[PDB]
Image (cartoon, rainbow over the protein chains, first blue to last red):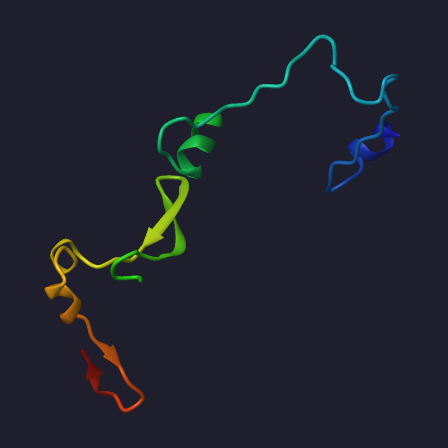
Length: 50
Length: 50
């Protein structure tokens, strides 16, 4: 299915099966939240993100 | 009130954080009751009243 929808579209369409326990860690990974602690606006934070 | 007690009226945006907006009489116009006189209310006719 992703075979079908990757190579043939103008939009990205991905297919997968659900994990066993319906809400958990991808084991070999993380979930990083980059934070603005001093007084800055959206521009500077997104810039830091990039 | 809004002269001598004050008025939280509305909210603004300081360096990224929502904070309050107050409008109150200045320093010198509310220490002694003489200052009671100095304050004027405007009638339906357009003319102030002490």
